[PDB]
Every structure is written in structure tokens, then in C-alpha cells.
Image 1 (cartoon, rainbow over the protein chains, first blue to last red):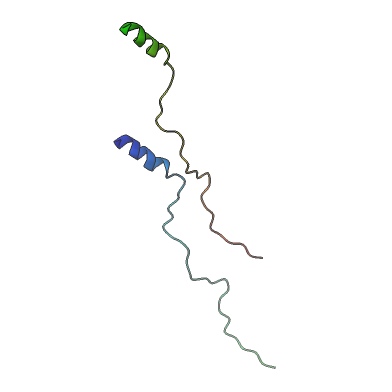
Image 2 (cartoon, chains in turn green, cyan; image 1 turned 135 degrees about the vertical axis):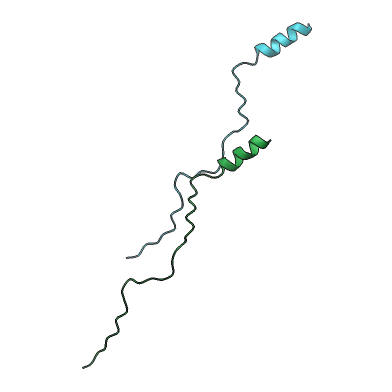
Length: 39
Length: 39
């Protein structure tokens, strides 16, 4: 049975790419403006 | 008759490859995407 177990564990895991990062929360698509308006 | 029986049992079994595994249900042809779309 020691063989058959390892065959199961290896058969049920393939293609799963770990990729320890998820996604970052910090977005900056465009920097902050910091300018004014007048008439 | 003890000889003839064993000849039958051996004659009627040949080429059958046991192969204790069948097929796995877990498929992963392509990993899961997890991305978005916008305009």
C-alpha cells in the first residue's frame, strides 16, 4: 500500500502552479495631480 | 483431474494486465485564470 498511496498523491496534483504571491493592493495608474483651478 | 483443472485456469488467463489503477478524475489541462476585464 505504501506504493499505491504515493501514486494517488502524485496523480491528484499536476498543473497547480504555486505562485506564492497573490496580488498587490497598491495601484498607481496615474500619479496624484496636486494642482488648482481658478476662473 | 487435479491437473486438468489447473490447465484450464491457466489457459483462460493470458494477456490480462492487471493495472490496479483506472483513471484519475482530477484534470488540469490549464490552470485557473483569475483575472478581470474592463472597457
